[PDB]
Amino acid sequence: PVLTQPPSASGPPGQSVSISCSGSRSNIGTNFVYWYQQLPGAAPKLLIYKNDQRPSGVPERFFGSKSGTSASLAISGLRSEDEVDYYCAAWDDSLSGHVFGAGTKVTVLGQPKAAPSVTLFPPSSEELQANKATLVCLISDFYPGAVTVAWKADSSPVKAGVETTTPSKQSNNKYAASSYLSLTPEQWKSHRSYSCQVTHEGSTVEKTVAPTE
Amino acid sequence: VQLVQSGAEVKKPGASVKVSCKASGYIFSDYNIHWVRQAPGQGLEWMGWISPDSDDTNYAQSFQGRVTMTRDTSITTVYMELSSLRSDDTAVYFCARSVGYCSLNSCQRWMWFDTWGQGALVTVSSASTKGPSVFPLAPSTAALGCLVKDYFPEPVTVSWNSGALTSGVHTFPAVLQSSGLYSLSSVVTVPSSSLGTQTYICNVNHKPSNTKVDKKVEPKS
Amino acid sequence: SVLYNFAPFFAFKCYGVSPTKLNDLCFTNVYADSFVIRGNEVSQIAPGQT
Amino acid sequence: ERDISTEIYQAGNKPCNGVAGVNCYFPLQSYGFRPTYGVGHQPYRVVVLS
Amino acid sequence: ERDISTEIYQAGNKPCNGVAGVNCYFPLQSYGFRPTYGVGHQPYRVVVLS
């Protein structure tokens, strides 16, 4: 069936790192196994076919081989192209078709720590005249991603209709999380204030703003 | 050569979605094709293969009646039909061409996907389709943001002062909603001395709905 | 019989007579030469390879 | 007498039942039928009469 | 056919007769064998029988 792969394997540049791909008796050992990599937001290509050779246009540093029921892939030289993920493609008879691994993430052995900057935005009067009130507070320019937003109604963590997304990698290799929570306008107007305290590696920044600012 | 394909958009569960892949350059009577999907948070999965010169059809061990193949030799296109779409099927479908030719079950040991094609992301969610709604926001350099809600479907383009403002513009990724709609925000970084002296305009465009709405953001005292 | 007890191998693909039938046919001259190469260079040690 | 089998043929002292690559080989091998070849590699459809 | 040599190879039109210039390189480059190197960068005692 499926094949076991390490979730993450990393190595400093200047030497080589090994990626393992095990298999059962009818997965690797009777059929050929192939290696696939894909660029982020692009299409996968061909690196290793028939377990020994490479197609044209591929550098000689990519080498892989198998001994028994498992296969290993070794890559030497990690500057800009080995940061992509790798897949272990093989064939078997139980599923009667091609099977793929879970996926190996390859990185290198570095950015300075960025303090979080949370800004709790109260709803404007244009929202109040339109009988709506959406409490929003966003955290930007933080690294590494470890934020946890808490919706506090000034005396107790209250969570109801909570939506929270994941941080995304921007062009500066940073993160920008987002979190909203919609309420009725009368419930927001009943609160005397609001606070969005985010815990990012212990550096919690207090941001309390009045409804009338 | 190029292996471009046509994608689709969000839809209600249980219906049928049509995606097509087009081939050109090479002769479409000697190469088998393969169809694989890639979802976020997981790896690649395989469904089946067909032949352009024959009526051969093969299925996966998990998708026997959920998906059916269709071939168009004269148009040199292949048409994929998905029936009874589930919730955990939001993936990117890739039109992959393999060298050689196989039809038997045991022939597949030598098959590798050589020439790949670009994929398209398709999702199946039942939600009201309509134009976007913009929610005003007040500021807490002073930072202020513009909120857009219940836009359907993806994507949206955000502009400030009809494109006259580019500095400080920073959009945010779309969050997930339990009601089926989508939400997005655009927070700009302006100096605090120009918060009320000069006033900016928040604009958003949604191509599938063919509507445009403009507003006038004003900070509160 | 004293050939396969010299640690597990890495490459034993052969391009001719089978290694198990070498006892059935008697030869007159066999050549022996050895060297050491990097593991990325074992692949191109073959008849007609670049 | 026809013979259909996908069992691995062993060519060493160690036994092979589901392992191959070092001294055991798959019995089937596929033809590389291409029209770019000459005369001695074209697929000839041969039918017998007994 | 084995070959042993010591003279410096010239990749251009510069006559080198004992020195290694810009286009003159030493034709004998040594390996490097460390435990830090991976599986595909390790010495294998490749022996061939003819």
Image: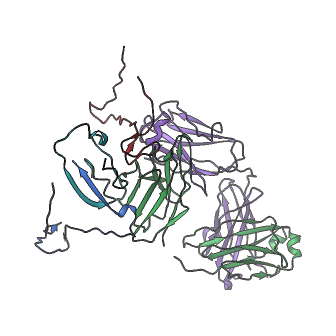
Chain colours: A green, B purple, C cyan, D red, E blue
Q: In the displayed structure, would residue B143 be above or below residue D12?
A: below
Q: In the displayed structure, would residue E2 be above or below residue B53?
A: below
Toward the top, the furthest residue is D50
Q: Is residue B143 left or right of residue D49?
A: right
Q: Is residue B79 left or right of residue E25?
A: right
Q: Going 66% across and 66% down the picture, which residue do you hit?
A: A166
Q: Going 28% across and 43% down the picture, which residue do you hit?
A: C15
Examine the rendering and report whether any part of residue B18 can be seen. Answer: yes
Q: Nearer the viewer, residue B144 or C15?
A: C15
Q: Position of residue A183 (x, y in %)?
A: 83, 68
Q: Position of residue C39 (x, y in %)?
A: 34, 59
Q: Position of residue B28 (x, y in %)?
A: 45, 36
Q: In the displayed structure, would residue B39 be above or below residue B24?
A: below
Q: Going 58% across and 40% down the picture, which residue do you hit?
A: B60
Q: Position of residue B23 (x, y in %)?
A: 48, 41
Q: Nearer the viewer, residue D37 or B8?
A: D37
Examine the rendering and report whether any part of residue B165 can be seen. Answer: no
Toward the bottom, the furthest residue is B193
Q: Residue A58's image quarter?
A: bottom left
Quarter occupied by the C terminus of chain A: bottom right
Q: Is residue A185 left or right of residue A204?
A: right
